Image (cartoon, helix red, strand yellow):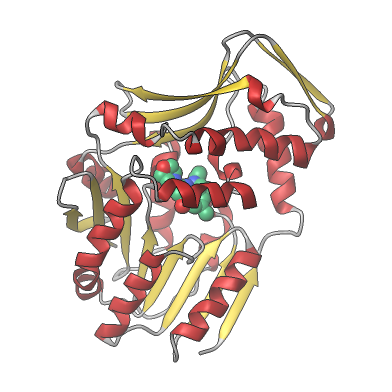
Length: 321
Ligand SMILES: Cc1cc([C@@H](C)Nc2ccccc2)c2nc(N3CCOCC3)cc(=O)n2c1
């Protein structure tokens, strides 16, 4: 099938965005950085390791559901077009593509992500694996370019991994509203949400004894040091995973041990850390079944299927426009 890739981001858009997030985030109280910047090359490779840890159940729990339910996804949505809000590199992507193709309705794959080189590799992989499928990769970001997704016949939008949990309620409602805005009647959204559960299990999933998550978290400082000529003493920042009971979310923090002064050279910026000051690097909201259905409703989408894994650890929602 034909491949296309459309790039709506400027060549330096990634670097401009990083400059903005860091100039802004290192000046908030508390300091905070968005989790999208964990995922450079080293960081993406560390994330792969995390998904294979015994502590980190979300990846396998979601794959367990999709292994068992992809055909039920395919029969309810009846999509001819799979839109992945993501890079399309995972096994789950092929599980859904396999199920739409088993149905015979699969015509088009639309991976939508911010890294055009990954999208190009993904498009070549799918083109080699799925004959007669057209791939229309779209390089754009959520806040501007969701309108540039092709119309197709009937579209299944896919947002897996409980990545929606990185948005707190305010931004999360804005995102779901905008996504529902670009969907057309007859489209559907497959959404993965990690579920509230025993808090000790949740912390463990974000602070494995082997230290992999700690290295993943510390890597954002390495990314800033490298990309913006900074002098974070990375090992002076301790990994801290917290359960926030009242907000029902995991939080990843980096805790300064002793006072630190950090100079970000590209930004002409100097910031100060108190001894014990913690900086927020990721929010991971955990959900309850009924609240996910209500948040989808508030955005204009109607949930028509809900599936958990055998342990009730992880949820998949299918919601139609
Ligand atoms: C390409 C990519 C990007 C992410 C980052 C950008 N997210 C995000 C999404 C919207 C807004 C802000 C942040 C990601 N986040 C994942 N998460 C797993 C569950 O716990 C924490 C979040 C998994 C995973 O594959 N991502 C893959």
